[PDB]
Amino acid sequence: DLFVPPID
């Protein structure tokens, strides 16, 4: 659910 790195 993260912006960077684009994961979760």
Image (tube, rainbow, N blue to C red):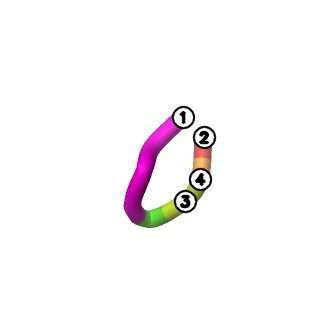
Q: Is residue 2 left or right of residue 8?
A: left
Q: Which residues are magenta?
A: 1-4
* Measured Cα–Cα span from mark 3 to mark 2: 7 Å
Three-letter code, disc 4: Ile
Q: Label 3: which residue?
A: 6
3 inside magenta stretch: yes
Report helix, strand or loop for mark 4: loop
What's the residue at 59%, 53% (across, down)? 7
**Circle 1 residue:** 1
Left or right of 5 on screen, residue 8: right
Instruction: Give the image location of residue 5, x and y in percent.
Output: 44, 65
| Image quadrant where one finds the C terminus | top right
Relative to residue 3, is residue 5 depicted above or below? below
Instruction: Tell whether label 2 touches label 3 (CB within 8 Å).
Output: no
User: Which numbered tag is attached to residue 7?
Assistant: 4
Magenta span contains residue 8: no
Amino acid at pointer 3: Pro
